Length: 49
Length: 403
DNA sequence: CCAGGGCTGATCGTGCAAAAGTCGTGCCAGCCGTCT
Image (cartoon, rainbow over all chains, first blue to last red; front, side, top):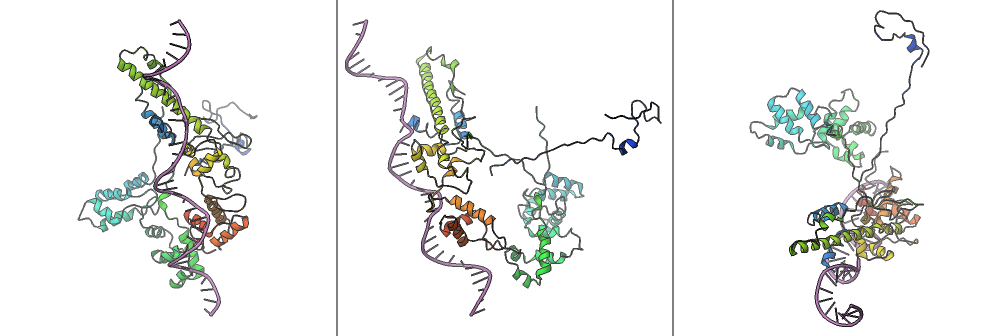
């Protein structure tokens, strides 16, 4: 994973029970960005006609 | 020259489908002879989809009823089948005229696939131009050549068309493009397939550039004499019983043996016709010698009929393609170049040469005959003409258009 | 009791000539691009 600066404190009930509040500076800094190389494929299935 | 054998050797000249079927046919007669996922997802496609739209729109009972009649006569390929008047007669009315049905049949002309259920080409295309923006440069031109003067357009000629219909060579040609970029047969827009069609038989061995007598996968009809019923033969009660059991046993043994005999014959029989022909595969579809059954029985160790019967209805299969054994039969064609040729090879060459030509200036018969003579084939001009017109290849002088 | 002759169930041969389909190939008719 990655190192992140944390602070155990309630914040307007956004971390109410087990939700993790995340600053906008984490999306801006391209942190926790993952790539996903999915790949489909089409066959030929030659018929008799 | 035998009954109990005359067929026992004509019972293989058919496909394995029927063989299995007749083998079952006679598998009941002889007691002693023997051998979730219900989630089928449904779909639509311009029948249900067409009907789907019908409900949404505001059509009255008499109109809705009529709608289905015409929406159900819409052939999947493209347009409707029967004529319009047909439809009036299949309502079963006298007060209802064509006008009443016209609307209902006119309203549908503008549904999912614009042009669906058109009938007689012209109406389809014409409608498609209606929903187009009227601020289109070639709007009036296209429409003018859509209502009339279509025959000429259909022909290879176009100069006579423009001179009569008050059209120029520059602008009018571009109007053509708007009629050309208009997709007739809109009914197949929401159409699709999902088929298969494939049969196995003798496969390939693939050994150092050679495929052969290989093996038999699943074509042997499990014919093992029953042993629980056979134990009662010798210890039969009456004469009736004993006779019965012995007759059925002898015939079973006969059939066992005839089935085994038929297997082997065709088993190693798939290696001499195909070898006598090692040019159509390796070299390609062009490069083909003439072969005859009479000549095949001469090469192999057997009679002509014997081999003709085995080869019939026996689809072969190599990683190079699957063709029926009987289809390999070809006539003759003098060449004078160390071996004769076939008309299928004429046809394939005509076709590969019409493919690689100038599109504007078409290739021809005497030209094709000359090209052939250049490569060293020496054929008639007729054979070429015939092989060209057999493949539904249009005339090349009529295949010309505006480059 | 054993070998010779007659009876009979087993076991073969998967062949062969006859009538029709097929294209090499020549003949013949219709049609269009061009120069007269």
